[PDB]
Image 1 (cartoon, rainbow over the protein chains, first blue to last red):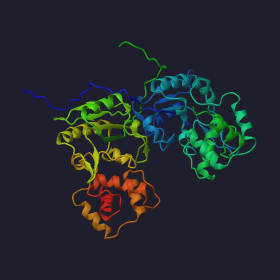
Image 2 (image 1 turned 120 degrees about the vertical axis):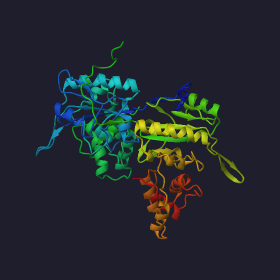
Image 3 (image 1 turned 30 degrees about the vertical axis):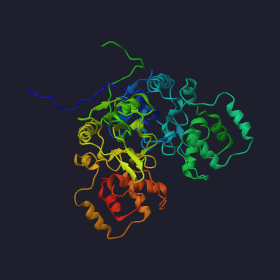
Image 4 (image 1 turned 90 degrees about the vertical axis):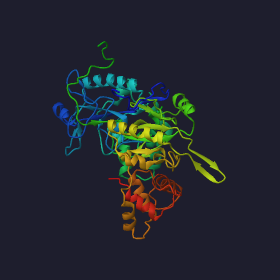
Length: 246
Length: 246
């Protein structure tokens, strides 16, 4: 002094062997709108995501929020007992109109081949860098069943499974589990137990109220999109047995 | 520079304004062991933390895990409905023996002025960088009331409160709240409701069993350590009103 030394002085001589990434899940969404309105919604006004996949050919991947920052895409959410997933997730939005109501039922919009071709390498890149296992790459509908229905019944989950990115029944397993069930439908409590085992937030009351029906429906929309009304049936029970968790 | 990306090609022309930190909470711990052994455990064992505050004079602050990484300090935990807090918290360990059981009962170990003088500016620095509010700087006992007691009944929470770091009753407020109560002890249900509002995982049964007693006790250990037996009383009710939640 001159100027005398003062202030904080961290000792950084030691670094722990036991640490990993704060990012534990990747969550997939659709935007429900076109490219320019997607960019509008995802940059101001309170909703955001880390990546946006455009609807061009080839499909542009925009980075909107750095991976080491928290984007606001999950809201009220739960997967495998982990709640409020924003802080521990990476969110990927895909340009897609979602659905339209018609007097005959909802009609959804398809995802392009180019979009799937851009998404798969992106997911491999993120999963490898953060050590994210396939059971933790899920949709907004998985973590907020009933409240959210994206990426919807037209999303080609099996294409992701083929690339090793999400759990999927092995060949012949659906048929084996159907034979195991032997035509007898398990009760609602059994469906609730199975869904929770897969990671879903679901009541364990043994009674089929809207909150349980919404969870059954989310699972159906992902694995048996032909019918996702949330009604227990034999095929859904077989899929609850057939889809791996490991 | 000198390397291209290992990942897919990205468009970075757009950046979202709606983003913030992945770090939501700061959790305080004591080590229950001496300085050199604490450094050993936190560097080479199953437990880790971002910072360690020594029991030397002045108190050395070690950084053991980068803030952008997940350390393993919280275990099964919940605060304000957020579960599994490792991925979303910064963990700070303080060298202190914790407690010791004797025939005259349990005894506790004090924290030193040197430790407090190192902890306060550290907390200010972290809280400012990550935008962490006072209600989210908490102890292991707060997030795991059934399992953990640290930092215990001797931890100087009020010193942190004087520096604007944690919630604490304003002068005169406890007396005013005691007066609003007008001699009437609220029922157990009311106690459970206030504790959940403050952030605790607590049953909502209206019955006073062990889990509710553990939570009332954790709150008492922090705000009324003269008695933390988990029993509802007028003073604890008054504190549940006087300690602000916003």
